[PDB]
Image 1 (cartoon, rainbow over the protein chains, first blue to last red):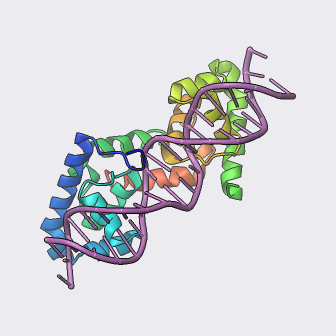
Image 2 (cartoon, rainbow over the protein chains, first blue to last red; image 1 turned 60 degrees about the horizontal axis):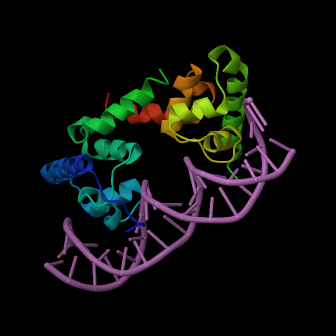
Length: 92
Length: 87
DNA sequence: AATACCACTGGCGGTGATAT
DNA sequence: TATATCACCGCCAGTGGTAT
């Protein structure tokens, strides 16, 4: 319905990429979805939604997660990385 | 209402538009066309009615030929921090 | 003319509980 | 325990129509 909009195919692949990085690294980083949520100031279901392709990433959340997982945003979402780069061109 | 800093940002932004409009041949509708939105929406931003976010601020900066920091140092800072994650 | 004003609404960005 | 999923929705940025 009207309340929530489904993600594009591209947003879906971005989420699969993100969740795989999280799985590969949650051990070495000592993470949990609940700790990630805390770091971001949301609950486990908010993070679960991003990881599972229910809610889409925005530039801000993507940047935060990249930092938490210690990767660059482009390793999961090249398109958001590029939107972030184009915004940067307006500051620099 | 928006915060005092958000209101200042809007005042800086409109001042810039007022000053460069003639040389750049702009109007609130043409700037709106350029951002994919309507005159009403643009007017709300210029007038401190709706808050600016990083994307719209970056578009506006490019349309006005200025840097984001010229109207909103706080947003410029946010932008830079996201970039720290793409680097 | 160009801009400002008004009432309104889709969908972003979540929540807590429950199921696995 | 950790995660995945479910029902649910506040809020406001942007709207189109109109007034100045």
